[PDB]
């Protein structure tokens, strides 16, 4: 049972006996145990020498000597046994050779007795040698550590982990040293080691037992080539052969313009424009001090128009109603598009072109339905685990919680629905994603990720306990030791803690700890706060019928999860989501709060009716109010709204939630201003003796029509210019609003003028109006209280200083601008998805995957093509997957956390003849056809390719012939690599076997804010451009070959890379024709134009500043609201400014006083008080996009408009206003 003598030249065993009686089980075919024989080494010649030279190249010692101690049977058994490990480690030949060197030194070395002590045997009967079942081996520490370190970084791209992580048992790749690695190699409990070998890594200073000396042989270093191999390992594979480059500085972040922040550019632009305009305006004032009729043209035209309209009022009302009904009739063809991708992004953007390419070539990205579960009040605890130290465990990991979650998951898997179209029950196995067995799938094949997958969703295995004696002490093993083992080493076929439990999921895939649990730091997997249950379903195109079935199943999923959410509030806090939830939640409340909004029309009707009358009695106001004109106003507004929506429905343009819930109420806030001002001016001007009411209304319309035309044109032009946004919802909003404003103006100049004529006709008869069968408080208040106060000599410099202070303060506050909109922001206030997004932001440890997709034009069959893509030994440095690996080493500068997988490296590795993966039938019915790795017959002794002196590279014919076999070969214990699961959907093959498109999957780091999605997009695009530029240098590459980074979030966040240049350019385009129309229409006074433009700039800057303070981010929706501000503020500025300009008072102060009282009262009572019921009613929206971006911004715009129009502007007109237009002075004097 031992080796009595071990001087030199002798070995401890030679012939291979039968099977090992002790283990009895295994994963694969094992290796028979050698029989003990202490005997001098054998003289190895002939074919035995050829076998030795091939199997163990570091034992051949000359042509004619080569003493060794193993038979041909042991050499063949060793060659069979190491095929799996060689299949994993062949990427770095130095590592493969070192591992094989260790095994063939143990098995066949002629100096076997110098380091091996046999300790335990089993007798095989009298006259027979006993078989060896346990022994120990002695090595130097430096030898084993160099051998380990040469293999320490070899990677498994398909699993995105280290190969050493599958070879160190309970210790993962993070905690594995040479001792643990060698202990795993000798541990028979894993189902792989044929016999028990104890490894002593005896140190050199240490004194050793009698004749034993530690082994110290040759170890191939990482970076050193051996002979003429030229197969030096790349540093992705061993981390010792690439030059050191200091970590790259991060790139200039998006939301920065040029070399400076975007807000700094905003301050520079607004300040420069303001100071230039102010300097020019004051220059004109001092020039006027040194110096000590288009209005009539439009007046005459509008008087003729008004008189014709007043002449025939019933006919024009008839045509107005006919046109309004004819346009509104288009609502029968209305179509609503509810998908987020369609509204959020343009159909011909860059991200959508990439999305279309990916979806066409590889299929759409699968639908992910997730559940996050945490523990409400359970405390943590300790567990004295086996093979590890004491481990803290979280409260959520309590066994009863896992049992009820197992009941939940199993209940969800067996959920079935009725399909009205298919006329059958749809179960999970009909629509689920399945990486293994895609066709003829079952429930056991569906992709479902959870912690419970470590126990293959089997209740009996979860509750199992076992007795294990380690270090001489018997203890108890339960599910927690399997959990810790799998969390550290997820690539385990068999656990060693007395339980033969696979660590793989039931559908055949490893479950990585970041996919099962979350809420941890470092490698403290047992402390995880939240558990994650993920269902992945196949996606399809929207038109395809299968999508409806998937949506029905997800609906049942949502109802079941709401049931389990309500049922157990005493144990868990649960967040959950479904793929269709985002589409359902955003569009849920379009209709629900619309009758709540409808009260604004009633409030506007009542305000217009009461404000224009209801006086002198306060008890007969029911008949003295102007009910007819209120009804007219509200009908004109509704007419414009319905006509605009109808016309766009007639052109096939769809509508959305930004149309239904916003457009009638913003148009309500705008449209009634012009008629309120017109009616007030009608009441104020007295009639001349002998004049008819038609001429009076004509003269009134001639008086006020240029300003109403100015406001309508300015707002309509601003909305149409605001339609340049790439976002379709905002584009549709802008076009609908523009058309509604134009049609509103056209109805105001025809139907309302006619209605005022008919109401005046009724008024002259001193009769009650249709429905209800020379002073005023506004003018007295403004004349006696407001105007003596605002224009007082001790007020005007204070108002000037206060408003310039406010402007400067808002320019400062403009620095705090957020760019981008969070997903939560879109949701309704009470949606369950808000909890889901909070749980994702706190508990996931990885982000979404990113696929670097290569288009057609790249020859993957050429050796130059393979070398510019692979990352194994002999591949070119700075290759595609090595660039991705390098980007993955610095996750904060480039938002990639997990290195890419690659079909090329696994294909080349699979083709390797030494890996026993690609075999051909040598004889029989299927001669020269593919022999699967699971065929255990003797018909498959011919490898796919021949042996080589370097890396394995096929020719073009071999590449095209063998690639469809690789892409359909399922992985198993015999061959780990294969493309059925990981790569079948990642390569597109045309019928001549050509590669049309290909993708390389990698994972982002967790992304939480809009800034993280935007920066991840920028860094990922920069990496893909860097890959594309170097791939284009390979000869034969098409000039239109590119690599692009598809991920599902790109179509939502692409727009935030350009939103600032587009927003600034759009605002400047809004400012230019506004100035042009107010300059040209009001009589070509440069002073008045500059005054209006400066006021609009101040209102806009104040709006942006206070927006930044409040916490409203900048995006396309805020942009269209600021465009609305630029348009709308003309209604607060232009009327007062024109009233000042058209005035005959000799001094600036008197003109400021009279313009302030008359038009200030009209502007206040009309514009402000009409704006409030519309805008304020959106504060009950319950959809956060409207509550935040439409209510708050339009409210701020209205208040700043009122503040600037009524307080600032009269004072500025008093100081810096235009001089007197002498043509009206002469007109007043001559006609006097
Ligand atoms: C020998 S050692 O010394 O080195 N140390 C011990 C070791 C090891 C080791 C080596 C390689 C790996 N993998 C890669 O590489 C593989 C990485 C991922 C792989 O692409 C994959 C497979 C399926 C899938 F959906 C998604 C991805 C992994 C592997 C997994 C499963 C597998 O086969 C399945 O197994 C299931 C089961 O057993 O339950 C059966 O149900 C299925 O039918 C059968 O297809 C073979 C290899 C993992 C562990
Ligand atoms: C006077 C103010 C307060 C409201 C006038 C505005 C109208 C222009 C709105 C109010 C009611 C809306 C309609 C009410 C509900 C629907 C049904 C809707 O169809 C669905 O609900 C299907 C939704 C789905 O399939 O998810 C299509 C839009 C439509 C016609 C809306 C079109 C726009 C309308 C007529
Ligand atoms: C008269 C015109 C010029 C403006 C009138 C509009 C006000 C009604 C707005 C303008 C600024 C707003 C404030 C800006 C800042 C905030 C912080 C905001 O919440 C935060 O971002 C801080 C909360 C936290 O995270 O601690 C709560 C609303 C509030 C008080 C806003 C309350 C409403 C205010 C006073
Ligand atoms: C080789 O292994 C044998 C088997 O254990 C060792 O023999 C035992 O050594 C211990 C050490 O004190 C003694 O107490 C036992 O009496 C020995 N004999 C047995 C178990 O039969 C032997 O010492 C080892 N030799 C070397 C060089 O390490
Ligand atoms: C292979 O890598 C090693 C380590 O990066 C290189 O450098 C050796 O580094 C050790 C540690 O300081 C020194 O003791 C050796 O003298 C260094 N040189 C050699 C030749 O071992 C080594 O140069 C690299 N070899 C090649 C060919 O690149
Ligand atoms: C591989 O890519 C081709 C196109 O390069 C895909 O073929 C298209 O498939 C869509 C439907 O999926 C058809 O509408 C197109 O007409 C097809 N075009 C051509 C040129 O054939 C093919 O489907 C992709 N492979 C897979 C498996 O989806
Ligand atoms: C859940 O796990 C148990 C293991 O305890 C499985 O039960 C074994 O099934 C095999 C195959 O039929 C039998 O040979 C064993 O005798 C069973 N063991 C016991 C204790 O009954 C069980 O099949 C698993 N569940 C499923 C659905 O496969
Ligand atoms: C990719 O490159 C390989 C060679 O690098 C091309 O294979 C050649 O194909 C032509 C076509 O008959 C043969 O005449 C050559 O002899 C082949 N060369 C070799 C080395 O085998 C292959 O055609 C290229 N791919 C494409 C799509 O053109
Ligand atoms: C891809 O990125 C790498 C690293 O960022 C670039 O390599 C550097 O390029 C600059 C010039 O752009 C050189 O001055 C440096 O010497 C290069 N090396 C290093 C280590 O910084 C590479 O050029 C990029 N590819 C392209 C096509 O621009
Ligand atoms: C292994 O042992 C079994 C049983 O003794 C025997 O049938 C088989 O041929 C042996 N194989 C090798 C390669 O030694
Ligand atoms: C479909 O499932 C429901 C679930 O209760 C069941 O009642 C019904 O009979 C099933 N239909 C078929 C055809 O299996
Ligand atoms: C494990 O051993 C202990 C100690 O005798 C014993 O009490 C317990 O029942 C054993 N467990 C099983 C499952 O047999
Ligand atoms: C829900 O909770 C009740 C007790 O609150 C329990 O009896 C029941 O089994 C739970 N599950 C279902 C599906 O009702
Ligand atoms: C690709 O790498 C192999 C490595 O052996 C080399 O032989 C071959 O010449 C390389 N091809 C090119 C085009 O450099
Ligand atoms: C190389 O491979 C080819 C085809 O697989 C085969 O015909 C040939 O015999 C092999 N060996 C040599 C030395 O060419």
Image (tube, helix red, strand yellow):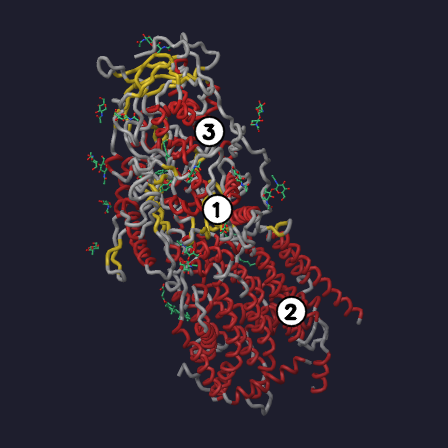
What is the crowding at mark 2: few (fewer than 14 residues within 10 Å), some, or many (at least 20)?
A: some
- SS for dot 1: loop
Coordinates of residue 903 in the picture (x, y in percent): 44, 43
Q: Which residue is mark 2?
A: 1075
Quote the CA–CA distance across marks 2 and 1.
63 Å
Do labels 2 and 1 touch, CB within 8 Å?
no
Asked where in the image residue 981 lies, by quadrant, the reply is top left
- Name the residue tied to disc 1: 861
Q: Position of residue 521 (x, y in %)?
A: 44, 35
Q: Nearer the viewer, mark 2 or mark 1?
A: 1
Q: Is mark 3 within 8 Å of ligand 1?
A: no
Choose mark 3 or mark 2, whichever is in front: 3
Up/down of 278 relative to 684, above or below:
above
Q: Is residue 807 left or right of residue 937?
A: right
Distance between the alpha carbons at the discs numbered 3 and 2 = 75 Å
Ligand 7, seen in the image, is in the quarter at top left
- Between label 3 and label 1, give the one nearer the viewer: 1
* Screen quadrant of the C terminus: bottom right
- The crowd level at tag 3 (other Cα within 10 Å; few <14, some 14-19, many 20+) is many
Q: Under tag 3, what secondary structure?
A: helix
Q: Nearer the viewer, residue 1137 or 897?
A: 897
Tell me where residue 799 sits by quadrant: bottom right
Nearer-N-terminus badge (3/2): 3
Residue 1066 falls in image quadrant: bottom right
Q: CA distance from mark 3 to mark 1?
A: 28 Å
Residue at image location 66% in from the left, 74% down from the top = 1080
Q: Is residue 550 left or right of residue 687?
A: left
Rendered image: mark on residue 95: 3
Q: Is label 1 within 8 A of ligand 8 (CB to nearest ligand atom)?
A: yes
Which callout, 3 or 1, points at the residue further toward the start of the chain?
Answer: 3
Q: Position of residue 899 (x, y in %)?
A: 47, 40
Q: Residue furthest top?
A: 210
């Amino acid at each position: 049972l031992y080796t009595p003598k071990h001087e030199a030249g002798v070995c401890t065993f030679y012939e291979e006996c039968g099977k090992n009686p002790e283990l009895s089980g295994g994963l694969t075919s094992l290796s028979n145990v050698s029989c003990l024989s202490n005997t001098p080494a054998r003289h190895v010649t002939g074919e035995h020498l050829a076998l030795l030279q091939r199997i163990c190249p570091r034992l051949y010692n000359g042509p004619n000597t080569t003493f060794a101690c193993c038979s041909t049977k042991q050499l063949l058994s060793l060659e069979s046994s190491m095929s799996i490990t060689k299949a994993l480690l062949t990427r770095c030949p130095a590592c493969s050779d070192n591992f094989v060197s260790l095994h063939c030194h143990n098995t066949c070395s002629p100096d076997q007795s110098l380091f091996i002590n046999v300790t335990r045997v089993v007798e095989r009967g009298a006259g027979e040698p006993p078989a060896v079942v346990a022994y120990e081996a002695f090595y130097q520490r430096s030898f084993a550590e160099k051998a380990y370190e040469s293999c320490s970084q070899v990677r498994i791209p398909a699993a995105a982990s280290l190969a050493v992580g599958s070879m160190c048992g309970v210790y993962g790749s993070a905690l594995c040293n040479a001792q643990r690695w060698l202990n795993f190699q000798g541990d028979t409990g894993n189902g792989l080691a044929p016999l028990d070998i104890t490894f002593h890594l005896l140190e050199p200073g240490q004194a050793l037992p009698d004749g034993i000396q530690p082994l110290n042989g040759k170890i191939a270093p990482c970076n050193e080539s051996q002979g003429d191999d030229s197969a030096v390992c790349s540093c992705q594979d061993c981390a010792a052969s690439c030059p050191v480059i200091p970590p790259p500085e991060a790139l200039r972040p998006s939301f920065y313009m040029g070399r400076m922040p975007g807000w700094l550019a905003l301050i520079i632009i607004f300040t420069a424009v303001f100071v230039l305009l102010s300097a020019v305006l004051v220059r004109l004032r001092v020039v006027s001090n040194r110096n000590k009729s288009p209005h009539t043209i439009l007046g005459r035209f509008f008087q003729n128009w008004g008189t014709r309209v007043a002449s025939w009022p019933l006919t024009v009302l008839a045509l107005s109603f006919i046109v309004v009904i004819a346009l509104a009739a288009g609502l029968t063809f209305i179509e609503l598009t509810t998908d987020p991708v369609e509204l959020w992004s343009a159909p011909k953007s860059q991200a959508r072109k990439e999305k279309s390419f990916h979806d066409e070539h590889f299929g759409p990205f699968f639908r992910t339905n997730q559940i996050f579960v945490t523990a409400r009040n359970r405390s943590s605890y300790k567990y004295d685990s086996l093979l590890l130290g004491s481990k803290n465990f979280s409260g959520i990991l309590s066994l009863d919680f896992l049992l009820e979650l197992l009941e939940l998951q199993e209940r969800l898997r067996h959920l079935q629905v009725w399909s009205p179209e298919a006329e059958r029950n749809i179960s999970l196995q009909d629509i689920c994603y399945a990486p293994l067995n895609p066709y003829n799938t079952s429930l056991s094949d569906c992709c479902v990720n959870s912690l419970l997958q470590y126990f293959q969703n089997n209740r009996t295995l979860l509750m199992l306990t076992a007795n294990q004696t380690l270090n001489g002490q018997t203890s108890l093993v339960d599910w927690k030791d399997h959990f810790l083992y799998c969390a550290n080493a997820p690539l385990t076929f068999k656990d060693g803690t007395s339980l033969a439990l696979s660590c793989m999921a039931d559908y055949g895939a490893p479950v990585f700890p970041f996919l099962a649990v979350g809420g941890y730091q470092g490698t403290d997997y047992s402390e995880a706060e939240a558990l994650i249950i993920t269902f992945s379903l196949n996606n399809y195109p929207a038109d395809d019928p299968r999508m409806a079935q998937a949506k029905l199943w997800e609906e049942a999923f949502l109802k079941e999860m709401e049931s389990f959410q309500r049922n157990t509030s005493d144990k868990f806090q649960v967040a959950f989501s479904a793929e269709r939830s985002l589409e359902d939640e955003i569009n849920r409340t379009t209709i629900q709060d619309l009758p709540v909004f409808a009260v604004s029309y009633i409030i506007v009707f009542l305000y217009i009716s009461l404000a224009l009358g209801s006086y002198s009695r306060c008890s007969r106001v029911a008949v003295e109010s102007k009910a007819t004109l209120g009804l007219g106003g509200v009908i004109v507004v509704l007419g414009a709204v319905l006509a605009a929506m109808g016309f766009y429905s007639y052109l096939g343009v769809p509508s959305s939630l930004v149309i239904i819930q916003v457009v009638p109420f913003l148009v309500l806030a705008v449209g009634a201003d012009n008629i309120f001002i017109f009616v007030l001016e009608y009441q104020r001007l007295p009639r001349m003796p002998g004049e008819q009411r038609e001429a009076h209304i004509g003269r009134t319309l001639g008086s006020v029509a240029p300003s109403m035309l100015l406001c309508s044109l300015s707002e309509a032009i601003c909305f149409f210019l605001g339609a340049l946004t790439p976002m379709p919802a905002v584009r549709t909003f802008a076009l609908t609003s523009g058309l509604a404003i134009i049609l509103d103006f056209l109805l105001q100049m025809t139907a309302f003028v006619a209605l005022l004529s008919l109401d005046s006709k009724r008024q002259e008869a001193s009769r009650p109006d249709v429905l209800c069968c020379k002073e005023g408080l506004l003018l007295r208040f403004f004349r006696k209280i407001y105007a003596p106060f605002l224009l007082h000599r001790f007020i005007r410099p204070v108002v000037m200083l206060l408003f310039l202070t406010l402007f400067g303060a808002n320019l400062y506050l403009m620095c705090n601008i957020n760019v981008g909109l969070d997903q939560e922001l879109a949701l309704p206030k009470d949606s369950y998805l808000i909890d889901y997004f909070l749980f994702l932001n706190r508990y996931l440890e990885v982000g979404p995957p990113v696929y670097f997709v290569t288009t057609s034009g790249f020859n993957f069959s050429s050796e130059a093509g393979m070398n510019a893509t692979c990352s194994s030994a002999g591949c070119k440095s700075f290759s595609l997957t090595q660039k991705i690996q390098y980007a993955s080493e610095f996750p904060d500068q480039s938002y990639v956390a997990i290195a890419a997988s690659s079909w090329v490296d696994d294909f080349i590795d699979w083709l390797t003849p030494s890996s026993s993966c690609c075999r051909l039938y040598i004889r029989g019915p299927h001669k020269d056809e593919f022999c699967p790795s699971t065929d255990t017959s003797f018909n498959c002794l011919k490898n796919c390719m021949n042996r080589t002196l370097g890396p394995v590279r096929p020719t073009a014919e071999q590449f095209h012939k063998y690639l469809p076999w690789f892409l359909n070969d399922p992985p198993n214990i015999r061959c780990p690599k294969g493309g059925l699961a990981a790569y079948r959907t990642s390569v597109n093959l045309s019928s001549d076997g050509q590669v049309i498109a290909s993708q390389f999957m990698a994972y982002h780091k967790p992304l939480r804010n809009s800034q993280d999605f935007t920066e991840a997009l920028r860094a990922s695009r920069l990496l893909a451009a860097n890959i594309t530029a170097d791939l284009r240098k390979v000869p034969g590459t098409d000039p239109n070959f590119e690599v692009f980074p598809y991920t599902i979030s790109n179509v939502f966040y692409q727009q935030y890379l350009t939103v600032l240049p587009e927003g600034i350019f759009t605002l400047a385009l809004c400012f230019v024709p506004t100035f042009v129309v107010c300059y040209l229409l009001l009589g070509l006074d440069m002073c008045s134009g500059i005054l209006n433009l400066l006021s609009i700039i101040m209102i806009l800057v104040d709006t942006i500043g206070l927006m930044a303070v409040w916490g409203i981010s900048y995006n396309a929706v805020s942009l269209i609201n600021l465009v609305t501000a630029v348009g709308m503020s003309v209604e607060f500025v232009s009327h007062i400014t024109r009233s000042f300009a058209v005035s005959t008072k000799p001094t600036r102060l008197e003109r400021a006083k009279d313009a302030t009282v008359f038009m200030g009262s009209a502007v206040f009572a009309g514009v402000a008080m009409t704006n409030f019921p519309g805008i304020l009613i959106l504060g009950f929206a319950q959809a956060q996009l409207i509550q935040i971006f439409f209510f708050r911004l339009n409210l701020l715009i209205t208040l700043l408009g009122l503040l600037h129009g009524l307080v600032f502007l009269p004072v500025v007109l008093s100081y810096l206003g235009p001089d007197v237009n002498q043509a009206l002075v002469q007109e007043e004097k001559l006609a006097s």
